[PDB]
Amino acid sequence: ATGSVPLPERLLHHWPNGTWVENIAVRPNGNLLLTTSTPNGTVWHVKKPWTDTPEVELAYNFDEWVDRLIGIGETTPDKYIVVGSRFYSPDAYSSHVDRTFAAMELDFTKEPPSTRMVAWMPEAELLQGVAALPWDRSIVLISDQYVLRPRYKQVDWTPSPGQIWRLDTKTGDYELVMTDYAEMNTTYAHGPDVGINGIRILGNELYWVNQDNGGVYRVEIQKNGHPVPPAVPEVVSVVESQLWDDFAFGPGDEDLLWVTGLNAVYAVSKKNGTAVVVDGVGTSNNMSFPGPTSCQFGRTKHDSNVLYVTGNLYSVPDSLLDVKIGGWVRAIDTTGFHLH
Amino acid sequence: TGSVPLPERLLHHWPNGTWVENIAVRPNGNLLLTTSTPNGTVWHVKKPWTDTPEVELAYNFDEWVDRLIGIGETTPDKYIVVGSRFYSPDAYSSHVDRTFAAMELDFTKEPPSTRMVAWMPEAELLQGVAALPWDRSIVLISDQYVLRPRYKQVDWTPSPGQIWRLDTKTGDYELVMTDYAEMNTTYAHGPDVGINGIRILGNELYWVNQDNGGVYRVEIQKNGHPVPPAVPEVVSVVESQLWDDFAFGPGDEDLLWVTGLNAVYAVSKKNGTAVVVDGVGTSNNMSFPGPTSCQFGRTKHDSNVLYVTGNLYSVPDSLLDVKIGGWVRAIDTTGFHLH
Ligand SMILES: *[C@@H]1O[C@H](CO)[C@@H](O[C@@H]2O[C@H](CO)[C@@H](O[C@@H]3O[C@H](CO[C@H]4O[C@H](CO)[C@@H](O)[C@H](O)[C@@H]4O)[C@@H](O)[C@H](O)[C@@H]3O)[C@H](O)[C@H]2NC(C)=O)[C@H](O)[C@H]1NC(C)=O
Ligand SMILES: *[C@@H]1O[C@H](CO)[C@@H](O[C@@H]2O[C@H](CO)[C@@H](O[C@@H]3O[C@H](CO)[C@@H](O)[C@H](O)[C@@H]3O)[C@H](O)[C@H]2NC(C)=O)[C@H](O)[C@H]1NC(C)=O
Ligand SMILES: *[C@@H]1O[C@H](CO)[C@@H](O[C@@H]2O[C@H](CO)[C@@H](O[C@@H]3O[C@H](CO)[C@@H](O)[C@H](O)[C@@H]3O)[C@H](O)[C@H]2NC(C)=O)[C@H](O)[C@H]1NC(C)=O
Ligand SMILES: *[C@@H]1O[C@H](CO)[C@@H](O[C@@H]2O[C@H](CO)[C@@H](O)[C@H](O)[C@H]2NC(C)=O)[C@H](O)[C@H]1NC(C)=O
Ligand SMILES: *[C@@H]1O[C@H](CO)[C@@H](O[C@@H]2O[C@H](CO)[C@@H](O)[C@H](O)[C@H]2NC(C)=O)[C@H](O)[C@H]1NC(C)=O
Ligand SMILES: *[C@@H]1O[C@H](CO)[C@@H](O)[C@H](O)[C@H]1NC(C)=O
Ligand SMILES: *[C@@H]1O[C@H](CO)[C@@H](O)[C@H](O)[C@H]1NC(C)=O
Ligand SMILES: *[C@@H]1O[C@H](CO)[C@@H](O)[C@H](O)[C@H]1NC(C)=O
Ligand SMILES: *[C@@H]1O[C@H](CO)[C@@H](O)[C@H](O)[C@H]1NC(C)=O
Ligand SMILES: [Ca+2]
Ligand SMILES: [Ca+2]
């Protein structure tokens, strides 16, 4: 063995070719809410994900406001902020359309669930991850980085600075809390990609991962969501080969982060940054995690130690330059795991 | 002399894929042309009265827009251009919703300067620009196209045709006219716009509607809103014509000159009588493939000359003939009479 690598894994559900599953939130009742980036910007609802073949249904298509959805984060219980924009095409390598990013709310405290525009954010480059402040959950932080001049045919790859916005979902007011940080930046060390990708908050520690340098970072944040001076990022862990996407603390209060990387998932010590691949490439179970994108732990007695992993690729490619989109959601049972 | 078809000549032809969309004539008489594709640019035609005049890229507006549509002069030799991001440079591509903007090209400086005047995300598709003659730092801007533009247009639900007032000094803007059948399209002429070009003469705002062949006008107050009850006056109707944009004149003459379906028309302001002067409908019927706008020369060499922009390679015989390939031409109107 219990806890041996590769950890036990199963497939919950697989979407058709062209469906890009990008992020995940777990509801208080334990069901999953998944964002998709293509073919449409939607949220899908996975019911009783601890069962063998859970039912899944479209919860809402956000076409009214966006072509694509990216990140999702819960605010007050069973309300969720999602982010997205218009995109030049549903193709996997398409850029966004500049100035079309927005934050929208999906309110599952009403049935049917209610949606609304929370904030157009034309000044952001590309909104990515969403993390509510634990003590003030109506306030969210949002990560932001991609090409500075997105166009129909991308030629100028000048990256925008990685940065993090504060959004007050009650008023729609937003402001930058952090920008101009090498730790949020990309230099395309890993090819065309982003710098800062997922963000998650635990207590008063804001964590993020960098897709281009394999760094995991954190910084202490004040009650208003701005960093505590001198606002210098603390390195948690560096695995230079890994194209980190998003992550989850836990389970429960284990001293660990669980992070999606390059066709694999890793456990990472919060104390000292020791990193161990637990499934996918680098283990004998090396075809089962093609292009994972995010992960979050279950929230019921059935699955508190189960890490639910989204992914967007049909098979493991020989090349990151010609992937094939076909999304999925899987489950990794972390019970008994130990770094060594 | 003055006979139809009026004398015409080509000043310059652009490569295939180049869509020349509108025109402003500078105080010194040179032409400033907007392009929609391949890029959003202004081209500068020097001494257009000469036989084969020189032309050059004045500014590429890529920093803010994939495409430019209309252009209108504000204070002397400053110009507002409008444009947005588009899903592709394909001739049939929709715009990307909420990316429209008005920018300024300042030709008083050397080299010409540019700035962003207003992002206008509430607008649907900005089209024609016309400054107020008594307050040229205020411009009216027409606006109509699909209500829900997308990567592959399937819902053709049209936006209401309307007109914005933009204060170029503050960047503030508000609607002054909306909810008018006369600015609307029902696609009587196929996928198109409703209100297209706008121009202002004195305190009279004119516009053409591309879908119903109508020419209209309303009186406007000094603050730029129409005089109540702001009912459009029908000026002329030619049902078959896909009007795009137009020019008053030349000089004192009681006429508008309007680009139509592969043709140009002179139109009486007093009574709306409409005479095709070049293109389809005259014996010289291939020389105006898809004209887009027109304005008169402003020098002693060409104040009776109507410079006409266009975006089509040739008059399309069938709907899959349409080849984008733009141009600028000149129609000498000297001696013309309605007859
Ligand atoms: C000029 O063209 C406009 C664009 O087509 C015309 O506007 C449309 O007019 C129709 C007929 O009245 C309206 O249809 C009704 O809409 C209501 C609901 O309206 C509200 O919700 C819609 C949907 O979000 C929204 O678009 C409206 O602004 C309202 O907030 C329905 O309950 C009726 O059953 C009926 O369908 C259209 O709603 C309206 N569209 C827009 C975008 O305004 C306009 O009538 C034309 N004017 C003239 C003089 O011909
Ligand atoms: C780097 O940090 C990790 C944690 O992120 C450290 O691993 C943890 O080490 C502790 C020992 O201090 C382990 O606790 C022991 O667990 C066993 C098994 O249940 C229990 O019987 C013992 O009484 C004790 O509690 C803990 O399991 C382990 N955590 C994980 C996730 O592996 C690691 O030691 C640190 N490395 C260095 C070099 O300090
Ligand atoms: C419809 O309206 C148009 C004007 O938009 C009329 O054409 C204009 O008719 C006037 C007659 O009052 C012409 O002006 C007169 O002719 C000459 C001008 O050199 C002069 O001898 C007179 O003193 C007076 O100015 C004007 O030239 C003419 N405009 C054009 C462009 O032809 C037209 O008669 C009206 N009706 C129809 C059926 O067209
Ligand atoms: C979904 O996409 C996958 C991957 O592109 C398709 O699998 C390929 O199918 C072709 C045959 O058309 C084979 O030549 C390739 O070797 C397959 N690739 C892999 C990795 O197996 C799959 O057929 C598509 N599914 C559907 C229903 O269209
Ligand atoms: C993070 O990335 C941004 C964007 O690449 C960097 O900002 C650029 O810095 C160079 C040199 O200092 C300037 O020439 C560019 O004009 C800047 N671009 C923008 C968009 O501001 C920034 O220096 C990086 N920060 C760190 C700490 O590495
Ligand atoms: C995606 O959204 C569009 C518009 O809302 C719709 O036509 C289509 O059926 C949706 N689903 C797809 C493409 O799977
Ligand atoms: C421009 O388009 C026309 C229309 O199809 C075509 O005949 C012509 O060859 C093109 N010009 C080129 C390819 O240089
Ligand atoms: C369009 O503009 C870009 C610069 O923004 C330039 O690289 C490209 O060559 C232009 N296209 C054409 C056809 O000139
Ligand atoms: C132009 O005129 C000629 C001569 O009558 C005719 O054959 C041709 O069809 C006309 N073309 C158009 C586009 O009207
Ligand atoms: Ca991501
Ligand atoms: Ca036009």
Image (cartoon, coloured by chain):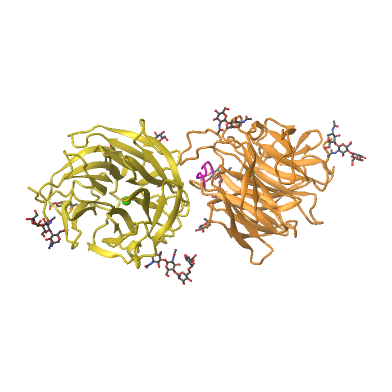
Chain colours: A orange, B yellow
Image quarter for residue B305? top left
Task: Work out which quarter of the rendered image holds the C terminus of chain B and state it.
Answer: bottom left
Residue A26 against residue A188 in the figure, above or below: below
For residue A126, side relative to residue A294 (left or right): left
Q: Nearer the viewer, residue A187 or B116?
A: B116
Let me know if residue A285 appears in the view.
Answer: no
- Tally of marks: 0
For residue A278, side relative to residue A316 (left or right): right
Residue A308 against residue A234 in the figure, above or below: below
Q: Nearer the viewer, residue B335 or B325?
A: B335
Whole-percent x, y for residue A141 in the image: 67, 46
Image quarter for residue A30? bottom right
Q: Nearer the viewer, residue A326 or B306?
A: B306
Q: Nearer the viewer, residue B221 or A116?
A: B221
Let me know if residue A297 appears in the view.
Answer: yes
Whole-percent x, y for residue B334 in the image: 12, 46
Residue B28 against residue B256 in the figure, above or below: above
Tell whether position B330 is magenta. Answer: no
For residue B88, side relative to residue B131 (left or right): right
Whole-percent x, y for residue A6 in the image: 76, 40
Give the residues in magenta.
A92-99
Whole-percent x, y for residue B93 in the image: 40, 49
Characterize the magenta stretch by its predominant secondary structure: loop
Q: Quadrant of ligand 4?
A: top right
